[PDB]
Image (cartoon, rainbow, N blue to C red; front, side, top):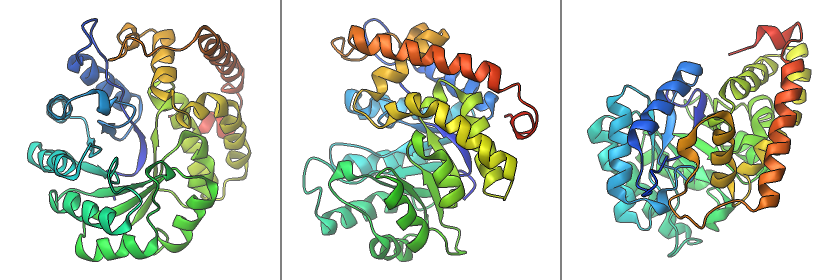
Length: 318
């Protein structure tokens, strides 16, 4: 699966001061991220504040990205199945390249029968678009090997598995699902598991949140991890070293305030458009702000010295 190889940021959505999405800025960051070495982008996902945005806003945002010539994977996350399917239908119509299928929420979540039918509806709405199933305990439901291949036998555009639930569930997917010579691939679904996914689970690519902030640094880690997955000794040590230093900033992808945390980093880096949220009350506390700026300063300081190192460090930049 080509659209699912390499490093793939999940774009956040820039609001204006009247807090309606800024699609021009979205297009700008999409272009820039690709220009930095990314393969594609995911929109509109949790990073993109989709529950805070209308389906029409998300569709316009996607169409703008696709028109701009950015490879796009469309997030099908929605309040119900019909609208989830709608995002999938629009995806294929505008000519989007990929489709992330998100489990059913709010109603009948932990019901596998309901999730199966929900999955089929989404996949059938875009039979020509390569698709990847998102799996997270946040949905109170776990897609196992039996369900995945029941779906795939009926929908050949299902060719990817994205895991969030932890190191153990990632191994399971690697063991029972994504390791056949079949085209099916494992994608990294959380920033803190880059090394694990690539070297221990045979992942094909990574969806990154911190990547929006530190693209060259995240790409650097993915290059080393893939090298380590190829048996490179020097890379295996360095990747663990870089993953360790990035762990704290990456760990924000795990918590609830991930959009708040990552939008503030973009502000530090110099992007004014990620200052205001779509809900004004949404803001880090003074403490939370103090914590990121300290850790953001720390990693940049550490990486400034470390990235100069000879060997795999030097060889495996972007």
